[PDB]
Image (cartoon, rainbow, N blue to C red; front, side, top):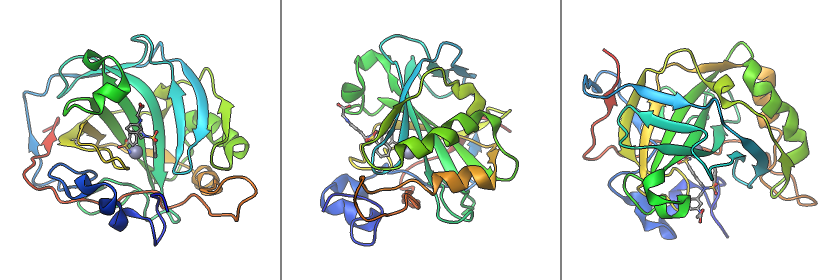
Length: 258
Ligand SMILES: NS(=O)(=O)c1ccc(CN(Cc2cccc(NCC(=O)O)c2)S(=O)(=O)c2ccccc2)cc1
Ligand SMILES: [Zn+2]
């Protein structure tokens, strides 16, 4: 009976194995746009993905991960609220069964159809596993998806999903450029939080972009054809793999923009 997004093993159950689920800096959160304060002091955000080296795509039974070579400073995130250099290790998404839900963060209680998480680790801790034990170990760049026009830079991802339908399947996924998943503006909100999946470690600086990307209904339909189950098991569509908003507690959300 391991964790997931079903009635019996979903977010409201996670605290029994992962008591930090009820902690002081859990994610996601609702971003109240009127309460978030412009912080002039946030340096520029620097997204340097020109040398990114993607390797593989994996269905992990919860989402799919696009994995990168993080054994050198190739694809890095710096600036904004961050001290030092954060290396891109993977990206993944969370999405809904319907276009009216799927994001983890919300904006004035609005749910987007999906949310992209670009996951980076602080190089001062040497490896990802050491980084997640630190309060400043990770920086996750979160990007909302709305349904409208297709995202050209997403299609290579969409077209490989048939080959990783079930849990534990992977495929080679070289030469994929994550710059094709960014919106025009890098205006953002930031706050200290957590992983949104078990083990729910309180190690993340969240950087949530204001501007959503547009994807087509055909693109998100292909996400919803993935499976949570393994091969030769009853089909469970991979949908609604999002944690709802958690209490803000003693946190302030800062805006990079006036
Ligand atoms: N949603 S999010 O952006 O907050 C976020 C969530 C989860 C992760 C990473 N995963 C869990 C993890 C966490 C800690 C240690 C280890 N291993 C220790 C080691 O590498 O020695 C693994 S996962 O299994 O790839 C994964 C699971 C579900 C959906 C997506 C990714 C990163 C960011
Ligand atoms: Zn995530």
